[PDB]
Image (tube, rainbow over all chains, first blue to last red; front, side, top):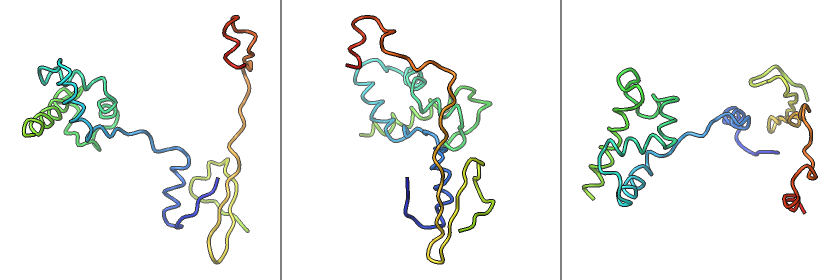
Length: 99
Length: 54
């Protein structure tokens, strides 16, 4: 197993090669469309429902794990993302409404 | 060529080489497994199941 590269970033690459960087959710983007689909399917009638749904997603799990990087306000107030999730949902539903 | 105590040693990792053109590094093979198990044979299965691996 070989790589050809610049010597500077190799240092960065070395860590990666040790399989270190984990799976980290990209549901930020695909949140919206998915949410829309769910709505269409005919069950998400409230933002509470949406929040509940989101809990089953890996994004939520990721947030719970290591929040701050994922745009997160604070853990003490939310506890289990019960405001953050809402915020996300709200964001989704304004844009969706507009379209 | 020579090797030095460097970043992410492990220290199971054990190679370094050099040139004035490019600084060339090698790494040995990943470790082979410790065995505290039975390599599960096929005959231990039920009858139909042994056509999993024909």
